[PDB]
Each structure stands twice: as structure tokens, then as C-alpha cells.
Image (cartoon, rainbow over all chains, first blue to last red; front, side, top):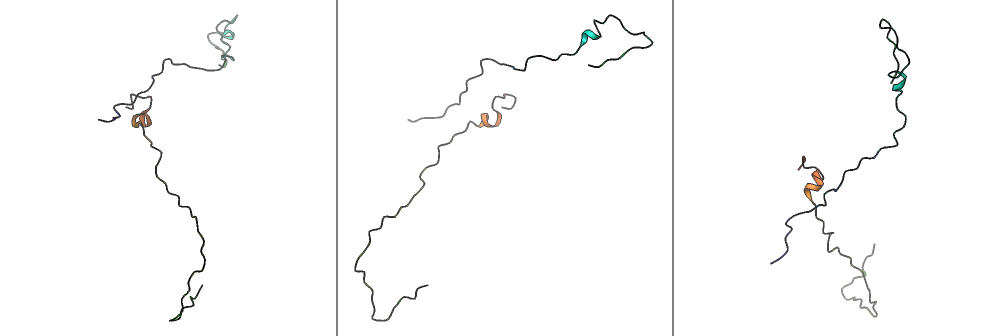
Length: 49
Length: 49
């Protein structure tokens, strides 16, 4: 006769959530991949991303 | 310092008294703490457990 600590229990998490700020300030890929022109093959031109 | 006024035929007898009321404080019990050892060491990680 008595009381015995058989186990410990935990509520398992029902969902996983991920939160970050509003997704502003992207790089200008249209200035390279959607450009109206591209440099000579002997003289390839570089920009920054 | 107090030299007691003893001599071989001298006695001091109380003629009146005070009832004191002191105060003794004793601890008796800790907080009955228990620990889920795996939650402390490894909580939310089966790869740790």
C-alpha cells in the first residue's frame, strides 16, 4: 500500500512555428538577368549582390 | 567586567522577579523539491536522452 512515482509526463508540442520580419530589401537581379544589354565576351562586366 | 561580591557568609536572594517571554525560531522543513533529471540534462532532445 502506498504511492509510487512510476513516470514523468510532458505535453508534446502540437505544431512548429517559424517567425521572421517582413521580407523587404531584396537584391536587384533584374539589373543583370533582365537587362536590355550585356558586355562583350572579351570584356565581361561585374556588379555587386 | 564584574567581580562578584562573594565572602564565606554572604548570600544574595531575589526579592522580586520578571516573567520573560523569549523567542526561539527553528527551521522544520525544506521545500519538497523534485527534478525530472532527463528534462534538466536533455529537455526536448531524444538525441541527448
